[PDB]
Length: 218
Length: 219
Ligand SMILES: O=c1cc(O)n([C@@H]2O[C@H](COP(=O)(O)O)[C@@H](O)[C@H]2O)c(=O)[nH]1
Ligand SMILES: O=c1cc(O)n([C@@H]2O[C@H](COP(=O)(O)O)[C@@H](O)[C@H]2O)c(=O)[nH]1
Image (cartoon, rainbow over all chains, first blue to last red):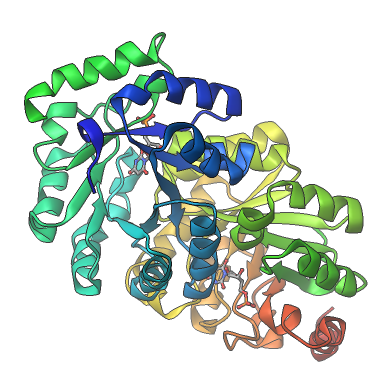
């Protein structure tokens, strides 16, 4: 997956007008947008096609899929029908739940990203202790795309170690949550940035600035 | 606690508005509480909640298995309650701050949170099972009053009931299609959740009536 400027926009505004305007303002800097439930539950799944029509960006559906296999399959089908290129799935519910998502993705020509450790403080309670095992489970299942935390670079490095250099790794928690763009890109293929861009006075200048700070990383 | 008619909640996971409305309408005399999840919402929009309230006046539990960071959890809960959901189902495994975020929105908006502590499928044994007692205890410490736990593992469901106490409200899926028994589950749960056994039946009303007949002495 070739992500322009190694930068994925987390578009978590909850108003169609604002989301479209802000994404338009930063379009020259990105070609990959992560759309999650804040926007989808506010404006509907049709917003995905709207983004493809307006921006011709790739779309990652950040739906944190975390149900039983039967329901996961249905969620993946609905999501890919809406035009998402990829979907983010939790590993904590186990291998069968992940495999259900991999099956649908294969059937519809899409990608699954496995979320192995999360970036927020609460992740330390239960997820962190399972995270290495979840990553190994991903490897066992043939997962090639992973998602891990900018806010703990040593944990992100470990994730990279487990999955190897051939796997693709994206990482949220940059900016607002305290993660550093350049340090994160030591390990991740691409950084995910939400509030630092979409809540900025000037989103375009915010994106431009981030990219300036990592310019020697590409 | 919510007064669930016949201790039976419909898991409406059909993905077509026409079929979902037909089936729900057919069992309305037996069930006043409907669990709507992402299969239906991602297919038909959040306005499906509005349509169910307009058509049936049923209580709506939004089964969104909320499992994000606190800031995103807050946004999801706000959007969900804005749409008319009475309650939302939240994962505990992302930790206390993520759960608290949902509780805070529910409190502000006058709605309810159900904490999912453990799951019914085989994969739940890998990571969730080992954390479940602590996730449940965390819920109690946070003041969670409503819980969601698996019918397919009676011993686990019993332990969850112990942890949360008799005053807490507990709903339980995995009845029917996944092998859980209605009566046995209601030893511990306040209400059972049933999806496929009802919504894939040739006569969903007869399927619901049959389940209720089997637990008649427990009503
Ligand atoms: O561990 C994780 C996994 C996520 O998907 N996310 C998501 O990544 C984005 C982070 O956005 P922000 O840059 O505003 O903090 C949000 O959409 C959040 O839901 C995260 O923050 N931490
Ligand atoms: O542990 C759990 C938690 C759930 O929410 N569920 C949900 O409960 C319902 C079970 O439906 P069914 O009766 O068709 O097996 C589905 O909506 C599923 O997503 C579950 O099966 N197991």
